[PDB]
Amino acid sequence: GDCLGWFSGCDPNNNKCCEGYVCHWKYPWCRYDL
């Protein structure tokens, strides 16, 4: 494992997900960026 993943939870200030995902304040879970 390298990144958190859309399934994993992350923060907007401490985003630790893989390219493509975004920790928008809207929700904790990593939301897609499409």
Image (cartoon, rainbow, N blue to C red):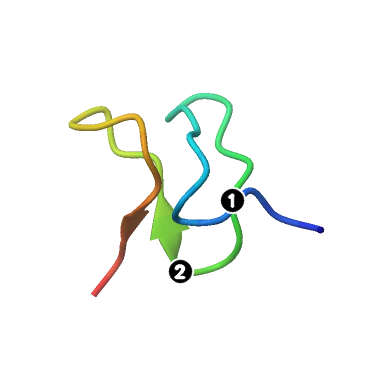
Q: Amino acid at mark 2?
A: Gly
Say which element carries label 1: loop
- Which x, y percent locates residue 29? 37, 39
Give me the residue at 46% from left, 51% from top: 7
The dot on residue 26 is none
Say whether marks 2 and 1 touch (CB < 8 Å).
yes
Left or right side of 32 for 15? right
Q: Amino acid at mark 1?
A: Cys
Quick check: 30 above or below 14?
Answer: below
- Which x, y percent locates residue 33? 30, 66
- Which x, y percent locates residue 24? 29, 38
Left or right side of 31 for 20? right
Disc 2 and disc 1: Cα gap in Å?
8 Å
Q: Bin the neighbour count of mark 1 within 10 Å (Cα to Cα): few under 14, some 14-19, many 20 and up.
A: many
Say which element carries label 2: loop
Q: Quadrant of the N terminus?
A: bottom right
Left or right side of 28 for 3? right
Q: Quadrant of the C terminus?
A: bottom left
- Of all residues, the one furthest to the bottom in this rendering is 34
- Which x, y percent locates residue 13? 50, 24
Q: Which residue is the site of mark 2? A: 20
- Of all residues, the one furthest to the left in this rendering is 26
Give me the residue at 52% from left, 43% from top: 8
Q: Bin the neighbour count of mark 2 within 10 Å (Cα to Cα): few under 14, some 14-19, many 20 and up.
A: few
Quick check: 11 above or below 7?
Answer: above
Give me the residue at 59% from left, 51% from top: 17
Q: Which residue is the site of mark 1? A: 17
Quick check: 22 above or below 11?
Answer: below
Q: Quadrant of residue 25?
A: top left
